[PDB]
Image (cartoon, rainbow over the protein chains, first blue to last red):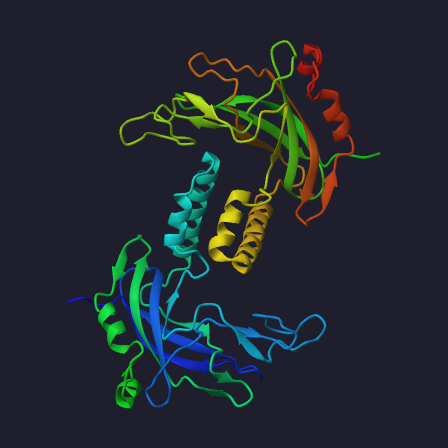
Amino acid sequence: NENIPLFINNSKIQYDDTPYHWPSNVISLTNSSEKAIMDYEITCLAYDKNGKPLELYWDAQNVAADGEVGSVGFSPAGVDYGIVTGISPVSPKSYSHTYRKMQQSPPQDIISMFEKQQGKAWVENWLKEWKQMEKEYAKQNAIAPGKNQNDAFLLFDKWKQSTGEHGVKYIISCVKQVTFNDGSVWKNSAYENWLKSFQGKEVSNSVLENYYK
Amino acid sequence: NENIPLFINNSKIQYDDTPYHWPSNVISLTNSSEKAIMDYEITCLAYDKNGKPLELYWDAQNVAADGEVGSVGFSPAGVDYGIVTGISPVSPKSYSHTYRKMQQSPPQDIISMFEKQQGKAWVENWLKEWKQMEKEYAKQNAIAPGKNQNDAFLLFDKWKQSTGEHGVKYIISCVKQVTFNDGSVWKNSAYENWLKSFQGKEVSNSVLENYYK
């Protein structure tokens, strides 16, 4: 048997405590393995209250009345960024989104493209040192063995701030892979089947309601 | 008058204590001020046995027999990276070189690379984080008030490992500017006259001999 090293306890829309009550997809995780987890890929799917699948702008940014995108607080002239007048897409609309822990860092496919580029010798050596430092920072920020934590991602699409209503009723998730601090990579052999069974498909309310029970 | 906050005690070639005895321009520096120094610009000129100026690949990297650049130790196939069989220029050849404690930015080649793959907003945030990160590091390792310290830089050009002689017999240096830990910048009003007085000009051995006494 294959024991999943990163346990998803739940994935749920939650709203913050401020008067603007911004929505986030909050994924409750537990590192059940004996190794620190330095990176992960976790795929989510979204459903309305009737079990129909939803296409989202999953990583859309908020827009403010003065056109500011992705800010929070107040503008210097006094415009309230807390009031979300619209959304600004980032990734294309899709039934699924894959969240990555080292999202702040460029993916390894992209770093590998940069290595293979023709350049000066000192430029390649600059990138090598940068790669390692990036890896060391991620190791210091790893999820420790046994740690429970929430990883939260703003989810503005289908939210109406004035009423607090969100078209998304259920989020179901699956770990695609994880990377441990020693560099080893665990891949979920059940992932492709899960994606094929669920992505863009209707799901019963009993399955959705009990998905994390 | 004007009193300098950063005093150069000496600049000379030193060799390390490995069987390859790689050379380094070692700059002995004293913070004569009352504030910690987080960054500097120091310009060096080089002169041969008879006080004639030398043009160097000041920041060139070492080449090994297999052709690797900037490497230390031993290759898998047993190539000795300590044997320096040539040099690989970085900056163009010049009478002068200006050394810095803190780097101003990532190489332009890499910034441009990154914006095409990550996008403009990603790069701007990345440059911001990178600047702060280098600034925090510079502040933690600043030269303390009153303290002397040696800062070393490899200097391969005009050097012959098989023989041990270095063509550079005198390095004469001058502070251009200094950055204190609060962000403020002091500029040396004497620097431009110094640079004009020396760069590309022959100078007597007696002047070179006694420059730091």
